[PDB]
């Protein structure tokens, strides 16, 4: 089976920016966040089980997840968050394996937010790349996007590994704080060459 | 298919879950047997095989790319940590693939055949009702030995891992006692539940 790099980092680290640079160089990319979105979209795989556990209040009239209603719940109620992840996480794993099985590139990258926090994701990957950046930058980036309160964002951050812990568990690191896109590309270029070599040797 | 009605069918090892399941399927219920999914995902190219290989090593991967079930069985019965690490891979994948199979089901309701049902908060939440196929432990022991060729001690170890008979029965919504019952006798109970399940399914829609 195909050589796999886990790409992780805290929320707001710019994982997608870096992931997209690897995809442009030929890496196959599996983004677990995108899968999570897909499976809760209209006719998404997770929807029958979500309806079963949470009921029709969380199913919009197009058949998709009512994301605002779910967001309000899971941020107020840790049992709820846990019940939700118990549905979506297994599906993410399966879809991840499906896509990896079909991947055509010389190696595959799994973009996974809670990677170093997971015995299973660490075991699954051949290497771990951490896209690192300071917490105040992470918060600024998330607030630019979907504007959670600093409160949802700080809650999400509190559930993540510490910065120091994630960095100590990396095999590779890219710091994406004030880096320009040109600067990130220099770093991805070299890692891409090294990843081609690791993959040819396995 | 919207608002799928789902029955969880369970019972201890040797209770004859498969006999009852097959009766439902002959009446038009869609069956999703999680044991078959377990086998599927440990076949060549099966979804569990990379994690199995990343975690246990290629000695547990047969020539065709499938799980070496003989080697794996030796390990997991002798080492409880090893069993838990296997299941940490297969169990989420089984639960996931169950959804995919259930989505394609064409019958009026789905029955999930699940050994470790009442033991699982996930499965309980997932099912509209739980059906327990029940019998004495003595009957379980005998059947499992005489037909699967398990050693007594493997059965008892499975029996020791699984919920008690009493706890299983107390968590049931429906019960079929399958001890000395003939096929015809089981079919009578099944015909009645099937009608009731059709009505539940129709209401849920
Ligand atoms: Cl499979």
Image: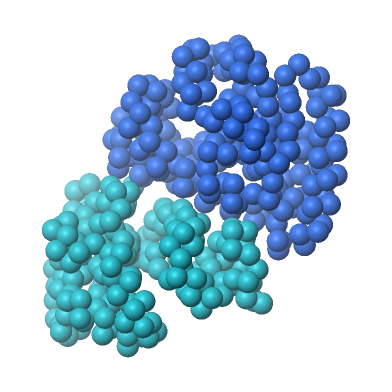
Chain colours: A cyan, B blue
Residue B41, compared with residue A34, is above or below; it is above
Residue displayed at 78% across by 54% down: B201
Q: Would residue B39 be seen by someone viewing this image from the given angle?
A: yes
Image position, residue B21 (x, y; %): 71, 34
Residue at (50% x, 71% y) in the render:
A73
Left or right of A93: which side holds A132?
left
Question: Residue A35 at x, y = what percent?
Answer: 45, 66
Task: Please name whichever residue, B50 or A130, is drawn nearer the observer in this view of the structure.
Answer: A130
Compared to B202, does A33 lie above or below?
below
The picture places residue B142, in percent across and down from the top left corner, at 61, 12
Please tell me in which quadrant of the rendered image residue A81 appears: bottom left
Seen in the image, is A47 located left or right of residue B183? left
**For this rendering, which residue is in front, A48 or B68?**
A48
**What is the residue that sits farthest to the bottom in this orientation?**
A144
> Looking at the rendering, in which quadrant would you find the N terminus of chain B?
bottom right
Q: Measured from the top left, where is residue A14 in percent x and y?
A: 26, 77
Residue drawn 74% across the image and 26% down it? B177
In the figure, residue A42 lies in which quadrant? Answer: bottom right
Relative height, residue B158 to residue B25 (above, below): above
Is B100 left or right of A128, judged from the image as shown?
A: right
Q: How many marks?
A: 0
Q: Which quarter of the image is occupied by the C terminus of chain B?
A: bottom right
Q: What residue sits 51% from the left and 78% below the top?
A: A68
Closer-to-camera residue (B171/B2): B171
Q: Establish if A171 lies above or below A157.
A: above
């Amino acid at each position: 089976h195909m050589y796999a790099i886990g790409l992780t980092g805290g929320i707001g680290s710019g994982k997608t920016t870096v992931a997209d640079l690897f995809a442009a160089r030929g890496a196959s990319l599996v983004d677990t966040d995108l899968i999570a979105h897909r499976i809760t979209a209209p006719a998404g795989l997770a929807m029958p089980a979500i309806e079963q556990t949470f009921g029709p209040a969380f199913v919009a009239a197009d058949g998709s997840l009512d994301r605002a209603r779910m967001r309000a719940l899971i941020f107020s109620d840790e049992d709820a968050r846990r019940r939700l992840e118990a549905i979506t996480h297994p599906l993410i794993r399966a879809e991840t394996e499906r896509e990896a099985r079909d991947a055509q590139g010389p190696y595959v990258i799994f973009v996974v937010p809670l990677l170093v926090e997971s015995r299973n994701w660490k075991a699954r990957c051949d290497r771990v790349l951490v896209v690192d950046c300071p917490v105040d930058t992470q918060i600024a980036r998330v607030m630019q996007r979907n504007g959670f309160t600093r409160e949802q964002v700080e809650a999400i951050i509190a559930r993540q590994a510490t910065r120091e812990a994630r960095l100590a568990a990396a095999d590779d690191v890219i710091v994406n704080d004030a880096a320009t896109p040109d600067a990130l590309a220099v770093q991805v270029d070299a890692l891409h060459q090294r990843y081609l070599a690791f993959a040819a040797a396995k």
